[PDB]
């Protein structure tokens, strides 16, 4: 009927390839490889000939850009079964790349995966081979690329971007520990790619290659699979201080949209939260400790001013913290946690707060016991954080481990937390977006503190001093 339309528009071609992704991976073990004939083996040789270029040294043709193994992290051996490159694999010529390298990349994923029943080594070296895009060391090294010499280089950028994100969504499931460490190398490559790509995209505006720098690669790009967590919550193979707080804003937006991008939340809330909170929790949990013990425990950029850990690693521990706070403010107890099944899964969920504090934390029936148990190390973390945007998640987080009532050791604790964080620094790692944290904080302290009319007496102490730009918030 409409396979002519896939010769009329490649949009519908990849869209069939990726609707086939959806119809292939969904009932992953019901729709059958024996039935897998129509699209089934329809593009094995249509996948190689799709983008698998010839793994050989010369790059002959025309472009703004001379081809290379640019990012071609071809970790494998010398027999060149690789080189499937977005230069000749799809774009140079007019267009083949912005359909299937995302779409039939996913297609080849599902097909090669459930074809031999989980043995995903068939498509394997396609990720160990270097998908050499154009040269990529200099970014504006031609700062006159005439929106195709540079804008086409950047659409090639977006192609390498979708290719990376999809390649990692492919690889990160299984881990033969060098394919696994390989995919870790891939996520590193994706971090560097996205950095340089947003640099070039910051060059000249208007570059959305819509095949699937904050959001303009975020909705218009690849699929943050919940498999992805199974790589990065796997204990931090340092990931990095950027490949945790850049490739972990994925899991941020996932919690902040699916549990308060239609691949990952095609599953449902309790169908999902049993991964994105409980299962991947202590792995993610381990990173939390390491982001204090260096970030504030021996918090060497706290007074030492080693700007590498201050302007490079600084926002790195920053990301790790604040993103860990979205894992509590949005993830730690949310607008449907208080339920029947949400309730029981939470009682089996934060009940892994043996490691939220020191060991022996899961020996108790009391839900108030665990509530104050994740209390017990929780405000103990209270001394580390960088910012009031990063601290005001501890009001949100601790109230999330509580909130039926206030109790002894909670109104007490919460008074302590609100008062300290009120008293602390807003020292530069200013406001206009901390005013929201200020409203949240003030109305947090002035509800835990026991003597209400007294707190205004403290406000008379504070008017004796005159932050005097945030005076309206107070």
Image (spheres, rainbow, N blue to C red):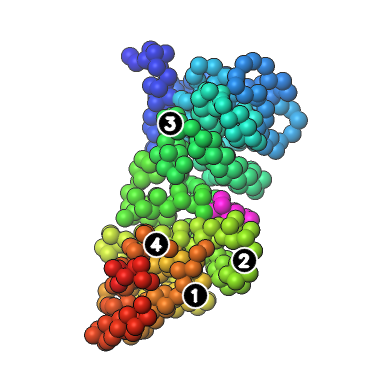
First in sequence: mark 3 vs mark 4: 3
Residue 390, position as x, y percentages in the image:
44, 64
Residue shown at 65%/24% (left/top)? 67
Task: Depth check: give the residue in front, 207 or 169.
Answer: 207
Q: Name the residue beneath numbered marker 4.
A: 431
Label 3: state its secondary structure: loop
- What range of the chain is rendered magenta? 237-244
Residue 300 screen position, x and y as percent = 62, 69
Residue density around tag 3, few if under 14, some if 14–19, many if 20 or more, within 10 Å: few
Residue assigned mark 3: 206
Instruction: Find disc 1 in the rendering and name its residue.
Output: 383
Q: Residue at x 63, y 45 (%)?
A: 185
User: Which one is earlier in the sequence, the residue at label 1 or at label 2?
Assistant: 2
Circle 2 residue = 305
The correct choice, above or below, for 219 with respect to 144 in the image is: below
Quarter-wise, where is residue 415 in the image?
A: bottom left
Count every numbered label the image shows and give the total.
4
**Residue 300 in view:** no
Q: Which marked residue is nearer to the observer: mark 1 or mark 2? A: 2
Q: CA distance from mark 1 to mark 4?
A: 21 Å
Q: Which comes sooner in the sequence, label 3 or label 1?
A: 3
Q: Nearer the viewer, mark 3 or mark 4?
A: 4
């Amino acid at each position: 009927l409409v396979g002519f339309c896939c010769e009329q528009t490649p949009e519908v071609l990849a869209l069939y390839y990726d609707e086939l992704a959806n119809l292939i991976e969904k009932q992953k073990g019901n729709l059958d490889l024996q039935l897998l004939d129509k699209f089934g083996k329809s593009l094995v040789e249509d996948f190689p000939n799709d983008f698998v270029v010839d793994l050989s040294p010369t790059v002959d043709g025309s472009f703004l850009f001379p081809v290379k193994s640019l990012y071609n992290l071809d970790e494998d051996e010398t027999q060149g079964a690789i080189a499937i490159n977005l230069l000749p694999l799809v774009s140079q010529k007019r267009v083949v790349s912005p359909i299937c390298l995302s779409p039939c990349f996913r297609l080849l994923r599902l097909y090669t995966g459930e074809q031999n029943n989980g043995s995903l080594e068939e498509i394997d070296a396609l990720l160990g081979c270097p998908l050499y895009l154009t040269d990529l060391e200099v970014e504006g090294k031609l700062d006159s690329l005439s929106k195709q010499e540079r804008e086409f280089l950047c659409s090639l950028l977006f192609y390498a971007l979708n290719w990376f994100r999809e390649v990692v969504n492919a690889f990160c499931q299984q881990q033969d520990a060098e394919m696994k460490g390989k995919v870790l190398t891939r996520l590193q490559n994706i971090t560097e790619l996205q950095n340089v790509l947003g640099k070039c995209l910051a060059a000249t505006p208007g570059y959305v290659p819509p095949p699937a720098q904050l959001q303009s690669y975020r909705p218009y790009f690849r699929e943050l699979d919940l498999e992805v967590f199974s790589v990065l919550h796997c204990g931090l193979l340092t990931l990095g201080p950027a490949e945790l707080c850049f490739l972990l804003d994925d899991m941020c937006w996932k919690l902040e949209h699916v549990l308060t991008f239609s691949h990952l939340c095609q599953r449902s809330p309790k169908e999902v939260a049993v991964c994105v909170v409980k299962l991947l929790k202590p792995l993610c949990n381990h990173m939390e400790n390491m982001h204090n013990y260096f970030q504030t425990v021996i918090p060497n950029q706290g007074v030492v001013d080693e700007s590498g850990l201050n302007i490079q690693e600084y926002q790195l521990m920053s990301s790790c913290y604040h993103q860990l706070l979205l894992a509590f403010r949005l993830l730690f107890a949310w607008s449907g946690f208080s339920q029947h099944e949400n309730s029981n899964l939470l009682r089996s969920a934060l009940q892994v707060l043996a490691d939220r504090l020191k060991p022996g934390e899961t020996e108790f029936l009391p839900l108030e016991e665990l509530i104050s148990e994740s209390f017990q190390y929780l405000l103990n973390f209270q001394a580390s954080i960088p910012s009031f945007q990063c601290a005001f998640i501890l009001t949100q987080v601790l109230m999330a481990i509580s909130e039926k009532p206030m109790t002894g050791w909670k109104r007490e604790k919460m008074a302590s937390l609100a008062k300290q964080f009120l008293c602390q620094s807003w020292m530069k790692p200013k406001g206009s977006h901390f005013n929201s944290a200020l409203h949240t904080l003030l109305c947090v302290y002035l509800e835990h503190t026991d003597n209400i009319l007294k707190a205004i007496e403290e406000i008379s102490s504070v008017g004796v001093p005159e932050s005097r730009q945030t005076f309206p918030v107070f």
